[PDB]
Length: 546
Ligand SMILES: [Ca+2]
Ligand SMILES: [Ca+2]
Ligand SMILES: [Ca+2]
Image (cartoon, rainbow, N blue to C red; front, side, top):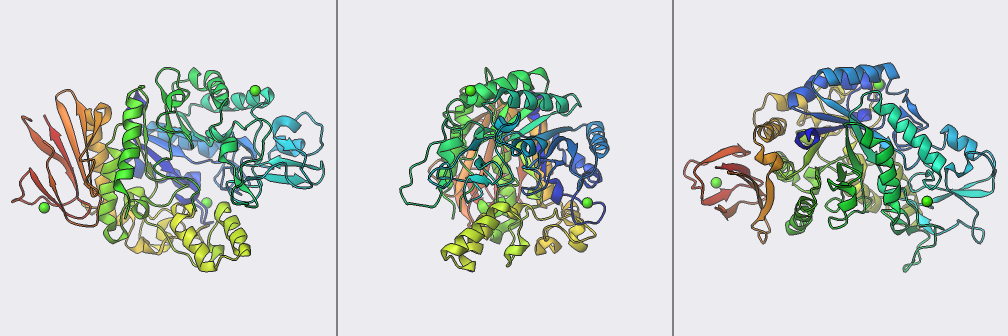
């Protein structure tokens, strides 16, 4: 229940803060900015993988689960981070990556050493078919989902990058070792896990070919390994052997789960996770804004989980997506839309997550060279598509509007060199607009995006209706206005958001003994009457009704 009232902040450590001038963010960097997060009002800190890794996927390819990435620091630095986080009245949850390991993980080095060895079926191996791969499955990062090993004359499976071989969850020895590793971290006193790619662990037995109606070289293989039948057997065991033994919060990255099939994931009775990251409103790995479509999706999840006593994880950004201002708002009304977006997703029923930079209203970036980018997915995509005849401009268009690297440029702290993120050369170039968008500037401006998030966190903590209140959608047919209420006892909160770059008129959806304006991003017009709302572009208002 503490995780229900919590506000979470997601840190992408490589791009948060560098403290020793090598252009790479580190743990001591995070430690130096804990005041910032504490003063923001953050309850829970989720940190992206900080384990030993070759960084072919920036930490999500782990070669040692119990050692810290050398770039980030040592185990002592982590211990210091956890100790300092805990003394500031905050909690830390780690990223649990157990769908796959690095190909440099000792398990896999042994696994690939011979066709028969005790670690061979720790991963997924298969002989080829017709001098080619076992099947036509495409990796999520493009190319074949199978990599050939010359020594043992067989292919190993990787849903993601080549250096990320999938673990074999049908092997009980694999599960046992993972369970031991998980409990090892929980014994250290961490407060839970974000469970990475957990919906990809069950493969369709036999790994059959998928329908290829357009005769591609490789086929998008979601129907082969995402939320496949039988996955709940593993997840239920995972909970029973690890999570259920501790007072922690677990949030599973569960791509491919819909609002009607979310029961055995997040239901109060029998659910394997406290909450999940669902992607129906986001869309992973796709290559104005129908506001009503967004209404339907978010409302489905609100109504759907309320019915089974589930709990929603609320978010608009993360390290795998583009910036929300570009995706849902407007760059022509950056400051305003960022606040409008904030109030929109933050004040729904669930636990809100804040990704680094989101509270500043950071936007996408446009680098001209493919060499300026890092995402293994888009680098592969460039290479493949260019060979097929796509122009440089065509591919960069996709990368700019869609590439997740938009969310991995350094955190913008001030107006100094590299926005104060590093004294050296950042691993990824800083967004040029840092001279306008940074923490220092937004701290002293009471109308900044940063201070708006501070107000949101504060009013949510002060009003139980904003935490446990029932959600109801208002004015569904309005293509510009997203309005909804939160109701708890004699308290009704009315959240109004003008999701358009234009002025809009809107009748107040009225029966109250008291009304109060909890938050607003535009100055209040004195002549304006409550019933006739004249909303500016991306104006948002939250009324409290008694
Ligand atoms: Ca560093
Ligand atoms: Ca089995
Ligand atoms: Ca007005």
